[PDB]
Length: 146
Length: 146
Length: 141
Length: 141
Ligand code: HEM
Ligand code: HEM
Ligand code: HEM
Ligand code: HEM
Ligand SMILES: [O]
Ligand SMILES: [O]
Image (cartoon, rainbow over all chains, first blue to last red; front, side):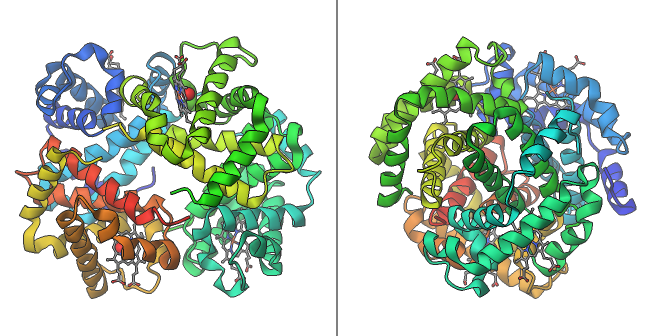
């Protein structure tokens, strides 16, 4: 995705402060609480019946770390999210059957979690840069759908 | 955009049967009838109080023809819609203030009008190929928005 | 909200569909899978080849449910209760997909009802499919 | 549909927003104009510069209407009727833009309510804003 030196610089410095283990865990649990229909892809994950249950579930936490660890990789390849995410795109279409619309919801919940965690430092312009990156990543992941 | 040779010949073949002026006025008029909010840019066209008044307004019909002649000329450059529509994108954003969502609505109302006009000849594969073309057009027109 | 005229328009276009409701339903599904492939992600267990019995039976179920909403347009939440619990609690289809099927349905009616698909009927049908999508979506969370 | 727990969450979250409601409404618009630049096509008459008094006064009107929405959570349609008529027949903002502002308001709330923006509160806040959006676009057609 095309970001300005200022956006890139925003995105990078902020992510240097993200503990992926914890944010991925919060991102994925809030996704499952806020838009429960996404729980369809995680039936074998435990009790996802209350916010508390979803949040403390270790499998949700372990997955969220995987998901944002992969997401972290794309940030370092912000110039070619397509080739970076092409194998996972195919994975999610052909084996996981994930409606790519979920990648957008996750991207928005992630922006929320970054706002909640960083508060005041997650300013309007910072948000803007992250908004283009999650839209970038979602598209890159929906790219091999057919 | 991403069209196979067969999709291109399906789009261009049916398009050769199109009375650009008639469909143009029809697609714009249906746009203004089915999604009345889009009438917001056309207060100077006059009477848009009924469906019959919209469809029959010579000013909608003349706008319809202009819009669809530009789309029609766009179909000759399916390999480069961004370049074909870059200035129009610039106009629509900085001078006309047209929310790109409206291009998506017109592209779907256009597909409906070609299905009404062509009937059985507007088969699922043909729809699919026009759906890519009207999403490509909607994307190239929104590309210069800032 | 559906106007009194919207209801009359819908009952006139649907009445017209009559016995083809099922063939239209299957044609709309084929149109959605071909135009909007991500919707196939909801049917990994179906044979989605053209003419497949599964698509034809599903299309028939889709139309009947639509025929039922026409018949009970003045009280859809209750007429569609069951389907809305099914879509909300079991199938859990993301709500964006409903706009894609309602568009494909509209295209299928356009293609088949040349005489009846006037501007105002088009408008009323679009609103109706919107309300049907709302009702099917209303128990999601 | 808003559950009594959702109303409780919304009231508690909103109740904490208190007199900052305006400042947050302005921050929410700014986030919106910067993240989704298409929404600026509706305010070609405003100075959308950070700090703009026009965005502040408008943020303030948006916030107060949401304060009235909260105060009338079991009677929103009626409480928001003139705002619904205004966006439907004069302003005519494409429905798609109400979700972009609802996302920006949610982000502004997350950034200012570290302790109160729990997962459950985030979910009831989204629901509430989707319901506000539904009411304001209900008279479009
Ligand atoms: C948008 C950013 C996303 C990224 C980078 C991502 C990345 C990943 C990775 C790396 C894996 C496999 C882990 C491994 O074997 O190494 C995976 C699996 C999976 N993903 Fe995604 N994912 C994303 C979004 C989503 C969304 C939003 C959903 C659905 C709500 C989803 C559903 C799943 C499922 C169901 C699996 C299989 C998990 C299992 O076997 O337990 N993913 N994803
Ligand atoms: C395929 C989609 C579209 C194409 C190709 C397109 C093309 C055009 C063209 C070629 C013009 C005239 C440019 C000039 O003055 O030199 C124009 C103007 C205009 N367009 Fe678009 N347009 C499209 C969609 C829309 C939509 C959906 C709307 C809003 C509902 C819209 C609103 C306008 C307005 C208000 C003007 C100015 C007309 C005047 O000043 O009389 N356009 N468009
Ligand atoms: C007009 C809106 C819709 C209506 C009236 C409708 C109606 C129905 C009905 C009547 C069934 C029950 C099937 C049975 O009992 O065999 C069903 C199931 C199903 N629907 Fe919907 N539906 C709609 C929207 C959607 C959308 C947008 C999708 C996804 C793209 C979706 C995906 C499903 C799935 C996957 C099934 C289960 C199929 C099976 O495994 O038999 N539906 N729908
Ligand atoms: C949470 C949903 C919203 C609320 C509560 C809201 C509320 C309001 C209020 C209270 C007014 C001023 C009414 C008056 O005092 O005359 C207004 C005006 C307006 N709204 Fe909304 N609004 C919402 C969403 C939107 C959206 C998403 C847009 C477009 C992105 C939009 C565009 C405008 C514009 C252009 C004006 C007039 C600005 C001016 O010229 O003064 N509104 N809105
Ligand atoms: O369905
Ligand atoms: O607004």
